[PDB]
Image (cartoon, rainbow over the protein chains, first blue to last red):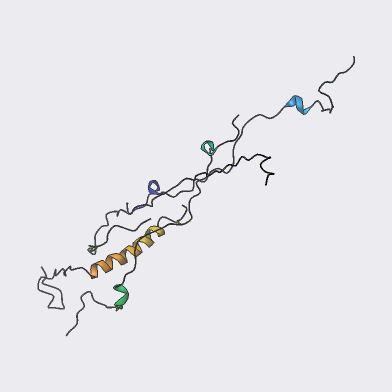
Length: 49
Length: 49
Length: 50
Length: 50
């Protein structure tokens, strides 16, 4: 064990992480943002023209 | 699609060290604690019998 | 952690030009957990008998 | 670090205790004096100018 303590000699350390995460992903959904939703009952829906 | 994520894949996993240190180094000092100090002025001290 | 090696023979002249003593760092000791599981698969008909 | 405040004072406290160990082990040794005076301890004044 050296008498002079150096950074490379330390064993107990606190990594000090960033405390968060950078996702950097796109979540825009321009089409779904518009086109108001509508609720139904059956698994099939129809309309007349 | 694994059922659950296991610890082997956690990119975090904080160290969770201990907040103390154990030192098994005796410091009894029986003799020194049974002598009594006495200050002097010179480097060479003497006494007569 | 631990203190220095077996002590003794510490006599230094008034001027010695200290030679970068060799203090040593701590020692890291780690362990891992272990899972203990006990499963019981009992029927329902048996859970009503006497 | 985890169980340390600073690497300087922490390393000093160790030596502050190691020196006590060095002292007692020396007081109980069989080491003799170092009479550099060369037969001039008999005089309070310094030894010959040489």
